[PDB]
Amino acid sequence: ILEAIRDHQVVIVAGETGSGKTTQLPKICMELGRGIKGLIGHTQPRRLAARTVANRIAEELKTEPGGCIGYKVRFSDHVSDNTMVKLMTDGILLAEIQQDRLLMQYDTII
RNA sequence: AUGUACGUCGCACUCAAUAGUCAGUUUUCUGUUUUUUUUUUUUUUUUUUUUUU
């Protein structure tokens, strides 16, 4: 899956219940070279689905939430300037449509 | 002046009684009194689900 993103502009990964693609796909992005020039967006259907996995990537990468791996849901802007991973639900990115139409804030959206 | 005239009669009530004509299969329901009032205005009733500068 690390090889598919460098060769294709849209990659689709289908996972099962115990797959873990929710927890390792942002880790693939920073390995490829993303995260620096733009933020790594990860769209989730629920905030508690988005919040729980946002603390998970920080704990797996031995950092704290709100720093490099931060989550932005309704007014819970735990985002610093040193961030690369930006967890957010489908409504948050839809709320950022009017602010940024071209989505110049990111480089990889999940 | 003289002489001159008299006798019998009838009526009523009535009036009865008569020609011929034989027969009609068996069985059945229908039937009685009594408490009487016929009618009493009604109520609020349940839940997949999930995301937004």
Image (cartoon, coloured by chain):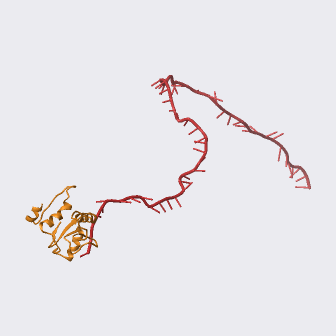
Chain colours: A orange, B red
| Rendered view: B25 above or below A9 | above
- Residue drawn 21% across and 61% down? A23
Q: Which quadrant of the rendered structure holds the C terminus of chain A?
A: bottom left
Q: Position of residue A33 (x, y in %)?
A: 12, 68
Residue A99 placement: quadrant: bottom left
Residue A32 placement: quadrant: bottom left
Hey, which residue is sitting farthest bottom in the picture?
Answer: A99
Question: How many labels were placed on the picture?
Answer: 0
Q: Nearer the viewer, residue A82 or A86?
A: A82
- Residue drawn 18% across and 61% down? A24
Q: Which quadrant of the rendered structure holds the N terminus of chain A?
A: bottom left
**Left or right, B27 with reference to A77:** right
Q: Nearer the viewer, residue B29 or A73?
A: A73
Q: Position of residue A55 (x, y in %)?
A: 26, 65
**Left or right, A61 with reference to A1:** right
Q: Position of residue B36 (x, y in %)?
A: 59, 48
